[PDB]
Amino acid sequence: ADLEDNWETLNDNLKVIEKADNAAQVKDALTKMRAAALDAQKATPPKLEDKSPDSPEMKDFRHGFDILVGQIDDALKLANEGKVKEAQAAAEQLKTTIRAYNQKYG
């Protein structure tokens, strides 16, 4: 279960919001992304630290993920307001986010 697995956690995530059936399972999946989100902070395609850049500037890298991860949970906020389709659309934003970013930053 190497880096390829972190992607798996994130995989089933888009899967459920896409198939949440109800705004209820949407909040659930997004709550997992919260976990899989910052977890990627220390487990992302570029693993940020590819050797030993500095070590403290790492949480700052969270600042970058904090942005993309910020609108994800905001979808969690919306789904609570009944944004089933809209929250799902925000889902394809996370998918292309990484690819558009150039496979995130790898």
Image: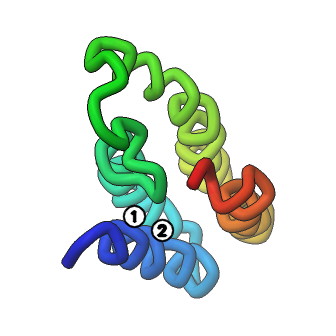
| Residue at figure coordinates x 78%, y 66% from the top left | 89
| Residue at figure coordinates x 36%, y 24% from the top left | 53
| Residue at figure coordinates x 54%, y 40% from the top left | 69
Residue 55 lies left or right of residue 47; in this view the side is: left
Q: Residues within 10 Å of mark 1 (few under 14, many from 20)?
A: some
Q: Residues within 10 Å of mark 2 (few under 14, many from 20)?
A: some
Check disc 2 and give the amino acid type. Answer: Ala
Secondary element at image label 1: helix
Position of 1 relative to 98 (above/below): below
Residue 29 lies left or right of residue 35; in this view the side is: right
> Which quadrant does the C terminus fall into?
bottom right
Question: Considering depth in this image, is 66 or 78 the residue closer to the camera?
Answer: 66
> Which quadrant does the N terminus fall into?
bottom left
In the rendered image, which residue does mark 1 sit on?
28
Query: Picture coordinates of residue 72 (x, y %)?
Result: 59, 47
Position of 62 relative to 20 (above/below): above
Question: Considering depth in this image, is 76 or 10 the residue closer to the camera?
Answer: 10
Question: What color scheme is it?
Answer: rainbow
Query: Picture coordinates of residue 52 (x, y %)?
Result: 28, 29
When asked about the image quadrant of residue 41, the answer is top left
When asked about the image quadrant of residue 99, the answer is bottom right
In the rendered image, which residue does mark 2 sit on?
24
Marks 2 & 1, CB-CB < 8 Å contact: yes
Query: Picture coordinates of residue 39 (x, y %)?
Result: 30, 48
Query: Picture coordinates of residue 75 (x, y %)?
Result: 63, 49
* Image mark for residue 65: none
- How far is the residue under mark 2 from the one under mark 1? 7 Å
Position of 78 relative to 64 (above/below): below
Secondary element at image label 2: helix
